[PDB]
Image (cartoon, rainbow, N blue to C red):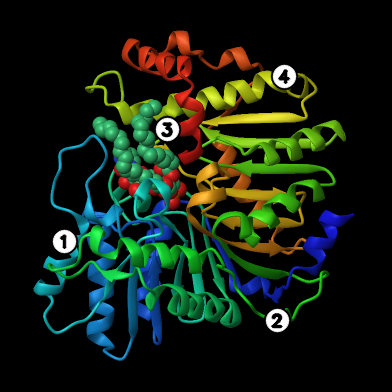
Amino acid sequence: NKHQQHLAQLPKISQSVDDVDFFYAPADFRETLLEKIASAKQRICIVALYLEQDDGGKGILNALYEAKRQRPELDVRVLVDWHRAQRGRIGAAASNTNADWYCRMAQENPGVDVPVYGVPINTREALGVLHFKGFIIDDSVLYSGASLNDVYLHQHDKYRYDRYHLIRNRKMSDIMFEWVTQNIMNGRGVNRLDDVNRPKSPEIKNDIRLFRQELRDAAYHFQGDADNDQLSVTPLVGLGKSSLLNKTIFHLMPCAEQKLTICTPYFNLPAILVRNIIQLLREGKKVEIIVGDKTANDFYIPEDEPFKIIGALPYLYEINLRRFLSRLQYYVNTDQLVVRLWKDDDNTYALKGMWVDDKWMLITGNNLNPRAWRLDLENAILIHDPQLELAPQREKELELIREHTTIVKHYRDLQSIADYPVKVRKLIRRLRRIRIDRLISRIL
Ligand SMILES: CCCCCCCCCCCCCCCC(=O)OC[C@H](COP(=O)(O)OP(=O)(O)OC[C@H]1O[C@@H](n2ccc(N)nc2=O)[C@H](O)[C@@H]1O)OC(=O)CCCCCCCCCCCCCCC
């Protein structure tokens, strides 16, 4: 079996069960992060899509400044997306940016250096973003898809559901930390957001081009020290067709002997992944797909509030799901295909991951969409648990993930375009007439 061989031959870093901690809620993740910031003695590397200027973001940044204040020799770095940091939300009131905020924070803390870098994966945000996940603190990585804001940290009443794994592993964290240092920190495109005279994009357009071309080769290189019959972790990083992550995602699915479970908050599977699923289904195996309700998509705008064009995305992601469910309705009937809609009032959904049987767990920022396949800098940690040492945590986590879901029993239980609000419905129909929906899909 060529797929199983790929996995068997992946380099693997030995992992102690006692150096792996699951957390099951945003608040716990927040507290853990604050716990580790205060405790860190060597380094703190925060890579995130963004670090918002809200109570959540402030909480984390204040704690970083405080850590550096009490340990000047501490190596503290924040890396966020260059483009995202220099704008407000799409279709919101143009405002003070996070980058401006980063500048005020430096000014307001004169003695203490917490460099905030901005990482452009492409010259336009829409064609590439920093989707590298990981908070690297000393010998450990607190790993999550979460960015740093109110909802992701559950600062107040609303939350955004992600996953949270802390892994103490000297070798892995070193590999991840050094990679970030070598391939991002010093690198053409990367500029400091905590500087009022930071450049604009026209000046670095060619720096970004060469940066992307070097990241096209983005990979980790390390010797394996663990065999395929012991708990291990395999850090994976990638961008584009050369991504080892994407190839590992590809080969994982067919390795399922019983069941595959997939999480994504943006359901838009590349054809090659859909074929994997169909294969599994045709072999009598089970496939579980846990996606958010459109109302739990962070692009969703309620009927109440004025409609904005970006608010059409969750509808498109649902169209994708309904089309996918309609094709495979037989397997829903046989109870092999289980599609779960997640919804918890107006809380939002951001879960990623793959589970292959009870043996592999992929924790990743990868949303298994065209964005991750072609555009964005993605990473992951692949946990191999052959002796089932993490079974209590795996089972507990999935139990909690599934709690606020309902199983789709037929595809027509999902709304069709006809049922959508008049402005959305109209917009979407026009896009489908002139096949623009097929085009936009590639950046979704
Ligand atoms: C009214 C004006 C109309 C004009 C529209 C054109 C404007 C385009 C320029 C901006 C392009 C943004 C690209 C973002 C890609 C990204 O973050 O990709 C990664 C992301 C998943 O990252 P993950 O780590 O999983 O985390 P999140 O899910 O929290 O990431 C969501 C990001 O999106 C931001 N956001 C969310 C809601 C909102 N209203 N505005 C925001 O800025 C958040 O602040 C955050 O940065 O994957 C995605 O986000 C998947 C969707 C990609 C969007 C594709 C480009 C924009 C749509 C296309 C234009 C046509 C309109 C639609 C017509 C049907």
Q: Position of residue 412 (x, y in %)?
A: 60, 12
Q: Amino acid at mark 1?
A: Trp
Q: Residues within 10 Å of mark 4 (few under 14, many from 20)?
A: some
Mark 1 sits on what residue?
A: 101
> Foreground residue, 222 or 212?
212
Question: In front: mark 4 or mark 3?
Answer: 4
State which quadrant residue 262 falls in.
top right
Q: Position of residue 394 (x, y in %)?
A: 66, 53
Q: Secondary structure at mark 3?
A: helix
Q: Amino acid at mark 2?
A: Gln
Q: Secondary structure at mark 2?
A: loop
Q: Are marks 3 and 1 in contact (CB under 8 Å)?
A: no
Question: In front: mark 2 or mark 3?
Answer: 2
Mark 4 sits on what residue?
A: 329
> Foreground residue, 128 or 274?
128
Q: Amino acid at mark 4?
A: Gln
First along the sequence among labels 4 and 3: 3
Mark 3 sits on what residue?
A: 296
Q: Residue furthest front?
A: 206
Mark 2 sits on what residue?
A: 223
Residue at the image position 74 percent from the left and 36 percent from the top: 275
First along the sequence among labels 3 and 1: 1
Q: Is mark 1 within 8 Å of ligand 1?
A: no
Q: CA distance from mark 2 to mark 1?
A: 41 Å
Q: Residues within 10 Å of mark 1 (few under 14, many from 20)?
A: some
Q: Residues within 10 Å of mark 3 (few under 14, many from 20)?
A: many
Q: Position of residue 192 (x, y in %)?
A: 25, 71
Image position of 168 (left or right of 111): right
